[PDB]
Amino acid sequence: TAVVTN
Amino acid sequence: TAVVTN
Amino acid sequence: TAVVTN
Amino acid sequence: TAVVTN
């Protein structure tokens, strides 16, 4: 699980 | 699972 | 599962 | 499953 906000 | 906001 | 907003 | 908004 990878969750990114950029 | 990969979840990205950019 | 890949979910992307760009 | 791939879901993309661009």
Image (cartoon, coloured by chain):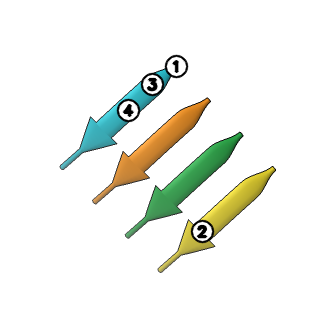
Chain colours: A cyan, B orange, C green, D yellow
Give above or below for C2 relative to B1: below
Please provide percent x and percent y for residue C3: 57, 53
Q: Chain of mark 1?
A: A
- Labelled disc at residue A1: 1
Q: Which residue is disc 3 drawn over?
A: A2
Cα gap from disc 3 to disc 2, whole angstroms: 16 Å
| Residue farthest bottom in this picture | D6
Please provide percent x and percent y for residue A2: 45, 25
| Residue farthest right in this picture | D1
Q: Which residue is disc 4 drawn over?
A: A3
Cα gap from disc 4 to disc 2, whole angstroms: 15 Å
Task: Say whether mark 2 and mark 3 are on the same chain.
Answer: no
Disc 1 to disc 4: CB gap under 8 Å: yes
What residue do we see at 74% from left, 55% from top? D2
Q: Secondary structure at mark 4?
A: strand
Q: Is residue C1 left or right of residue C4?
A: right
Q: Chain of mark 3?
A: A
Q: Secondary structure at mark 3?
A: strand
Q: Is residue C3 left or right of residue C1?
A: left
Kind of residue at badge 1: Thr
Please provide percent x and percent y for residue B5: 32, 56
Q: Is residue B2 left or right of residue C2?
A: left
Kind of residue at badge 3: Ala
Q: Chain of mark 2?
A: D
Disc 3 to disc 1: CB gap under 8 Å: yes
Disc 3 to disc 4: CB gap under 8 Å: yes
Disc 3 to disc 2: CB gap under 8 Å: no
Disc 4 to disc 2: CB gap under 8 Å: no
Kind of residue at badge 4: Val
Q: Is residue C3 left or right of residue C5?
A: right
